[PDB]
Length: 109
View 1 (cartoon, rainbow, N blue to C red):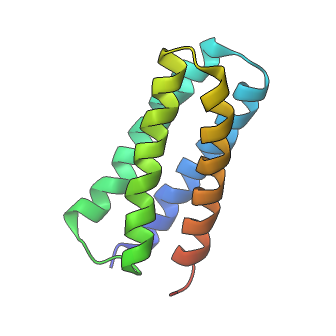
View 2 (cartoon, one colour):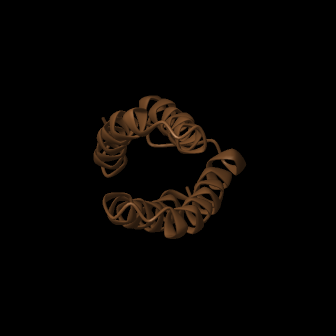
């Protein structure tokens, strides 16, 4: 099953993501790096559950889930490259994807 675990680890990941937004709006790169690491650890923690037991609530959710991870990677790449423009764009795509995954995960689409 692990659907409960995915939820408990997803909530915390999302919560960290929400925290990431505040720091982003505050332009505090110092706090941002620390949280980015925290988020990455949570991603691994949540993803590892799916890697262990590949059940999922649906295939689309898994596809968007992995896609979100890739977007997160690009988001960081833009931070490392100092690309402020892409950060805003990727952030919007990250939020939309995250909101969609949660919606799907709470039910079966």
